Amino acid sequence: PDSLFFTDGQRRIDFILVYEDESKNEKQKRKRQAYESNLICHGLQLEATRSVSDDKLVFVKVHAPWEVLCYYAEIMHIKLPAPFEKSRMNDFYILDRDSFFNPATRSRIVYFILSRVKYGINRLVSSGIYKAAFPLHDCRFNYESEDISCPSERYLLYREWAHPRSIYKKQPLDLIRKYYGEKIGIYFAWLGYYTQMLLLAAVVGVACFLYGYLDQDNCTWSKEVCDPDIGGQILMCPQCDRLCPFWRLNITCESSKKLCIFDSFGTLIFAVFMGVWVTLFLEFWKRRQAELEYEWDTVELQQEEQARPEYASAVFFWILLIIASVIGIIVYRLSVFIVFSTLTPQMATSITASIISFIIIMILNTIYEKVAIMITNFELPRTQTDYENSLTMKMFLFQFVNYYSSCFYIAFFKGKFVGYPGDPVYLLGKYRSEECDPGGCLLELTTQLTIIMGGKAIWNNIQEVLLPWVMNLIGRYKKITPRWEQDYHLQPMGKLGLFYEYLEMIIQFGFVTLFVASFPLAPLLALVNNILEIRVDAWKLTTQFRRMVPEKAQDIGAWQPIMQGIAILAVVTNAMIIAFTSDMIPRLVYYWSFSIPPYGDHTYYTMDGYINNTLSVFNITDFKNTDKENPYIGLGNYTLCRYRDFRNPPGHPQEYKHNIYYWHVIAAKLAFIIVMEHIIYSVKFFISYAIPDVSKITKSKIKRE
Amino acid sequence: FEEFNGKPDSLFFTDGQRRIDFILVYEDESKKENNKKGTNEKQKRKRQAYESNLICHGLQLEATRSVSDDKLVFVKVHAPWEVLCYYAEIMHIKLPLKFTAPFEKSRMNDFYILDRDSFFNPATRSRIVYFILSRVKYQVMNNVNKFGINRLVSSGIYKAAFPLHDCRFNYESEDISCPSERYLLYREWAHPRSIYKKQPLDLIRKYYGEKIGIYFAWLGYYTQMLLLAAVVGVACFLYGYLDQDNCTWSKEVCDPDIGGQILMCPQCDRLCPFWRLNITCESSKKLCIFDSFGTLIFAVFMGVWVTLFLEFWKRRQAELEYEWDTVELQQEEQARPEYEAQLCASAVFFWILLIIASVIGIIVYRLSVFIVFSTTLLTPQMATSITASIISFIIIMILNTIYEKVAIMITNFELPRTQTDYENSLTMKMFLFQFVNYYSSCFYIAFFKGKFVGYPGDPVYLLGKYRSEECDPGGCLLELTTQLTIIMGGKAIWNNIQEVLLPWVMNLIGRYKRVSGSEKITPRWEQDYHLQPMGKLGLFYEYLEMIIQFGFVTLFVASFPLAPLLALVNNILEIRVDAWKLTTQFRRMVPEKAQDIGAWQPIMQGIAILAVVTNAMIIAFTSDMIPRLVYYWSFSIPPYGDHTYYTMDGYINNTLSVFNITDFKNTDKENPYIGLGNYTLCRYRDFRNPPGHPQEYKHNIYYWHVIAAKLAFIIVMEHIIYSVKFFISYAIPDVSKITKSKI
Ligand SMILES: *[C@@H]1O[C@H](CO)[C@@H](O)[C@H](O)[C@H]1NC(C)=O
Ligand SMILES: *[C@H]1O[C@H](CO)[C@@H](O)[C@H](O)[C@H]1NC(C)=O
Ligand SMILES: [Ca+2]
Ligand SMILES: [Ca+2]
Ligand SMILES: [Ca+2]
């Protein structure tokens, strides 16, 4: 039969206490017997049934007496499965005296009973008293349950919302929380809304990218870079010590033509628009959170204090973060170094460098996870919620640095403070600073960013779930045991599965919002990843894992502060990216100021001559001020070389000092930073303040009565 | 009813056991009715129905004829147990126990009950009876229900309705049982003989209720924090003052061999001649005083101080909310739509009026300066600055009332939902109008004066014949300081004089309109009726003046370190000014309870957030500290300068730019300068290349170095200050330890 009720008995089970017979250490048998006897004596039904699949395994099942269960549920602030009270027995319409209650709530009550009972379920399992304790699923996802009385909720939810055949179908949050709990419901609601407006971000980003794409023909500076008569004649200086010749600037036609895509006005407008998209996300999410909190049974009081089975050094943690960021930076730098020490060539080298760095990030991720777990266990938190909050902050900071160290270095600290070839900078000693090509390092920042985004999303989700699904797909294209035994054969989520899910989503949100200027198509990848992830998470939760006790919560958790921090950091990082990593400001300044007779020689504003009239000049006879061996020996009969910097030419009264163009450009950069940051912050404040003028609709729904 | 018994200060009924809680005053028909007698008899019927419903609800009443004017009748009121306890229960009025709860008849025996007039304070009794008066109705016409005491006074049915003071402020009550709280309040709190003692906020709350106690506690705490800021600002100004012999650039300006030789260039078209820079020695010394590093340190300290002030006020507000147990009646709240009631177009109209207000402020300041300059022909320049500021302030005060009235009209055209919405709309509109009207000239001087005027060859005319003004080599910071101190001091002085005088003269006018040689005794109600009404807005204007003062103190503290000292002196006076005017020249405002100061808190947070950016902009653009630092660190050196080590020597001569007098181009007015025919070149205040040169008069590298330094300073200071403010807000728990202990 394998029914959900007691064998030949009209009573429903709520937890399975499986123990192994001693027959194949009397202390363990005595302890288990005492614990089981006390549990039964407390007023909970008990029965032991031999496993059909294996005779050795003797499973123990329980029940829920109606009166005691209802009373102890009333012990805590629980509403109707609208407070529940026998004096109001007739007030609430009841389909049946013994099955009206939600099985999820019944399992929650039995779990609370087990938790409060004292002589440690996890402690007993560690000592062997109870091998496991879990509730039961309604029906098999493979084939429907034999008992017709079962509504078959699990398989229905599977077919409707987990299987890819419903990839485009809407998310049924109703059955989701009614079956699993508030945690899963709110998680999936947040993820769905996240995707919903990632669609808007993606469409705007695609529009901007296409606008950039259509203007390859009119990209004047790239054309000048390519014309051999102009670009080829320019002979740039070597960018390294012993392993680089004097090179023409035109060898970078492919790089410049690609970079003219991601470095146009489209990118600037897209960054400005994302500046307000982020605040729209936050504000509408607060709206939806209020809506969900009111709609659902989310008015349950919380305990003042809680116990925990287990029960300054903060500066030491900061040292760990510092060494983590430095290790990431060094990992990327050595990766690029080793791969270089050996269209297609340079781009492939950069791609392989990014891949190697991301691989090393993945291997180090486990190390940060373990060290964070150990250091947070060292404090021995008294309670639980504080433990999850500490884990969230510590794990998030480790992931943040481990994932953004390379990107931040490539954006801000690469080629930003290298001097002219006469007096180069060695910040650490015998460690020359790498310098970007005339276009800038924006393109290879974008490469690193996209590689990390993709690689993480794909590899993680694929390797962690899609295995059985991919073997099933390959096959497609190219004895009776009770429910408790089958559910035992499954494995549990542990205590941090939802935590890891929020970690993945928050890291993705960081990728898509922090460096959005460099890569405007990041929202598209985030959208595709989320469309995959919703169904992947639903499938794995409904299929591969034991039943989870529901929990009560109103907010996503300790992440909302992290979301706001990410947004307020993203605005400034985008401003800095556009100001410094990109070269939009220097070329605008040239267009508007240095193409006019006082400085230029054209009769109108134009981009003509930007490259030739912006590159500085260097004098080999000034090869070095230390008068040591120089890289300019040999390498042809060349006399003068040009480098990417704004400095006075040789023979000027101020020999190789920053000229007026440098200061004009830097003033323009700072003006852009301040004006854009002030505009964006002002608009964000206005949007936040306009909740009465914006989101009145759902508050009106609440207030209508 | 019956006539006056003969005890003037007796606050009881004629029997002597019933305490009076309100006096309703109306006009009898015995006067010569005019226009429509039907309206008169309709008013009679309405008032008769009102009093009938009042007596039905259980309020005892009796009337009396005014001794002098037979046409005036004063209708007393009184509330016994039944109604008093019932309405206390419905309004959840909390009574002293001893963990405190509202009052219910089910729980009479659990209270510290002594006697009716004893156990309930007269303020609470007056508030209860006022709520009863407002709830009660009298009749219905036009298929609409009509109720409320306020509508009776609005329609002229009732002249007034008010509670009564315990006794005269200057004389004790003859009734020994009387507390004579007004006497003690006048002797200790008001009457500046106690100009120094800390005010007894508990007695103020007892007498006038929390609406006044909160304002006065806010003012006291404000004054203490102003004392802190004033001491620090005096230290900074004093350090700037003790360091003048070391202010090298001013020594250069005054030196008759460096500053004197520099032949500056004419500023106006033809109304002013060439001049030598050493005529500004006094201005240079003043700028050394007001433009040192002490000003920067004080700007940073004020950035911290505003946040400390806000946080400690929040802590004080929480403590006060606990101590005055206002939480329950703050929760118990309801509002009724105004009987005056029964679009975005108005919003855009108000915004347009705001733009015009700003433009008119700028224009009036400019015209005042222009006329004072034209009239000419103990420093003459200082006298001109003071005179221009004086006329500007006079016109600003004149236009303040116009903006007051137009804001009232604009908000009335929009239909408020209720009293609170109306009051918040007034808060917003009045604050925006006053902000523009007062700070437009200051912002103009700070940011838009002598900033976009070209070299003398090609001046920047706004639209023709209107040349832009320019400052002296030091800058217009001293002009800004003079304007700001004049505006602040004049506003304070005129406001205090008006506040003290106007109710006094109006009271004397009312008294003299009754020249009858009475020389007799009059009852409490009749003599309280002659006092001023204190219109329903209340402390709105008091908060408005204090908030404008807060704006002056914080927004421009980078140019005037002594602003907190003026604020402190003004507040030390204002405490007793407001206390006296309230206790001695006004009828008892009906008490009520308030949570916080009100709609002004968002205003104060906005001012605090804007203060940082405004101060950064002032220090960067209005002042000349940044060019001085750039010259010291980057232009006193061999690549550009000649000095072996960093120094400020030669700053003035090397910074001032050069112009070739014959190089005035354009065909219009070909003889603007060459009339004098004295020399062939002039020095002007700008960073531009000299004559000749590939780029004759285009901005030179020094200009862009300075601009980059300015923008970098703005970024650094704004980010650092905001980060420090956020960390300070996070660190402060925002509630006292003891208060957390209590509950
Ligand atoms: C670059 O310029 C050189 C010099 O004229 C040249 O011969 C070459 O064809 C050009 N293009 C590339 C891709 O190198
Ligand atoms: C400044 O010096 C000049 C010449 O050295 C002199 O004529 C002038 O009188 C001095 N200043 C004043 C205010 O007199
Ligand atoms: Ca996952
Ligand atoms: Ca005043
Ligand atoms: Ca006042």
Image (spheres, coloured by chain):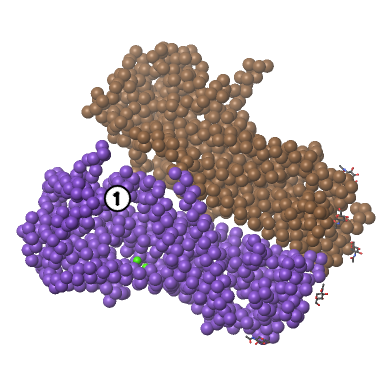
Chain colours: A brown, B purple
Which percent across, then down, holds residue B602?
43, 54
Residue at 55% in and 22% down = A166
Which percent across, then down, holds residue A454?
65, 35
User: In the visual, does A13 lie left or right of B329?
Assistant: right
Which percent across, then down, holds residue A696?
43, 39
Occupied quadrant, residue B434: bottom left
Res B709 visible: no
The quarter of the image holding the N terminus of chain B is: bottom left
Categorize mark 1 by other alpha carbons within 10 Å: few (<14), some (14-19), many (20+): few
Q: Is mark 1 within 8 Å of ligand 5?
A: no
Q: Which residue is mark 1?
A: B330
Occupied quadrant, residue B394: bottom left
Disc 1, SS = helix
Residue at 26% in and 25% down = A91
User: Observer-nearest residue: B599 or B221?
Assistant: B599
User: Observer-nearest residue: B279 or B110?
Assistant: B279
